[PDB]
Image (tube, coloured by chain):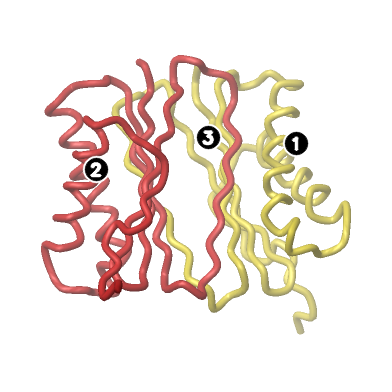
Chain colours: A red, B yellow
Amino acid sequence: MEGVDPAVEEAAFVADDVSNIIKESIDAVLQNQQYSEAKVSQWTSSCLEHCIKRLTALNKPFKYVVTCIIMQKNGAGLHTAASCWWDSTTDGSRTVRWENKSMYCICTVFGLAI
Amino acid sequence: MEGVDPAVEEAAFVADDVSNIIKESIDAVLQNQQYSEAKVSQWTSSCLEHCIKRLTALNKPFKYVVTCIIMQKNGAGLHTAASCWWDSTTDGSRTVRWENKSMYCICTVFGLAI
């Protein structure tokens, strides 16, 4: 009763504004062409440019970061770590996990308040 | 003519001040105890706290971020992506890759100029 695994297991709860841009971008940055390993990483890189470029067009918020991590297969181990200093202004961090069949792609948009 | 693989293949070229703190921290955050899978990720998390806490003691620079990614084994696939908005003040990004025998641990310190 599955067949396909499309955004079946999304992560975090990003705002509507950023959630749509980032996701719509993956939809295009990943569906634009066929599954290419050379693109398996470049994909998300283009999304980052297609996420940042869009956020600038919308200009809201102002200061925002766009990072993502590619999860090759399911058996592969992936773990990131990050401890930031003090900065209430630059606080957002909204991660999302995209999935299709097996390969997973996580992308987090950091909505920093100026 | 190898035997061991300790920081054999370091990444980037972080400043002396941050390079020592971060590395000295891994040395402790990873050598403090025995190799534990439960700690394989918590390790770098403690380093992040032992990196951030130190940077505060040194208070230089001021605004700094501390993130890291764990590379389980060598066959496992790991890829991160991040596109940030405009901000010349918050620009540093210095990554380092630690290695011992097989498991790799990357940690990047973001030295932001206030």
In this rendering, which labeled residue sits more in front, label 1 or label 2?
2
The residue marked by circle 2 belongs to what chain? A
Q: CA distance from mark 1 to mark 2?
A: 33 Å
Residue bearing the label numbered 2: A22
The residue lying toward the viewer, choosing from B88 and B70, is: B70
**Pair 2/3: label in front:** 2
**Who's the residue at 30% across and 73% down the image?**
A1
Question: In terms of image quadrants, where is residue A91?
Answer: top left
Circle 3 packing at 10 Å, graded few (<14), some (14-19), many (20+), is: many
SS under mark 1: helix
List x then y, in percent, for residue B46: 74, 42
Could you say which is closer to the camera, residue B65 or residue B16? Answer: B65
Write the residue at 57% across / 41% down. Answer: A82
Q: Residue A27: image x %, image y %? A: 17, 55
Position of A28 compared to B83: left or right? left
- Identify the disc placed on residue B50: 1
Which percent across, then down, holds residue A44? Answer: 29, 55
- Three-letter code for the amino acid on which mark 1 is drawn: His
Disc ID at residue A57: none
Question: Can you tell which mark lies on residue B110?
Answer: 3
B21 sits left or right of A114 in the view: right
Three-letter residue code for mark 3: Phe
- Quadrant where the C terminus of chain A sits is top left
Distance from Cα at disc 2 to Cα at disc 3: 24 Å
Q: Are marks 2 and 3 in contact (CB under 8 Å)?
A: no
Q: Give the farthest residue toward the front.
A: A1
For the residues labelled 3 and 1, the Cα–Cα distance comes to 15 Å
